Length: 92
Length: 7
Image (cartoon, rainbow over all chains, first blue to last red; front, side, top):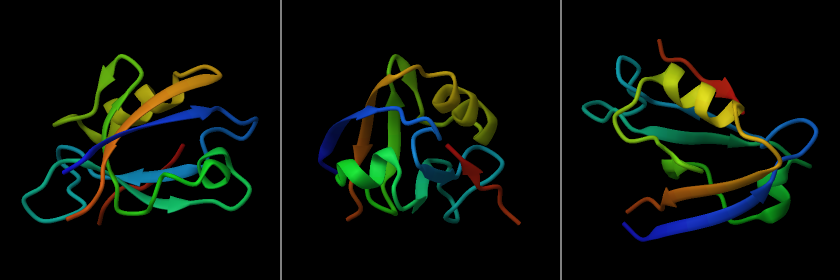
C-alpha cells in the first residue's frame, strides 16, 4: 500500500513489538510476509506511535524483509543498534 | 501453529 518509513530509537528492552510471518510460517494463508502482531506498552514503537498491529514489515535498516523466513527476520531486527529505519506498509 | 517473536 503506502510505504511508511518509521524512525525508531531502540529501547533498553528492544524495539517493543512482536512479529509473525515468513517463509514456512505464514501469518495469513498464501502470504509469506512479516507482520506486526503486538506492540507492547511503554516500548519504543508504542511511544513513537506510528507502528500498528497488522503492519507488513518491508525492511529494517539495510536488510530486506520481503519473502524471508521467520528466522532471517528475527535476526535482522535483533541485530540492529540504537537507531532503526523501519519500512512498513499499512493494511488495505 | 505459527511462530511469533519478540523484537
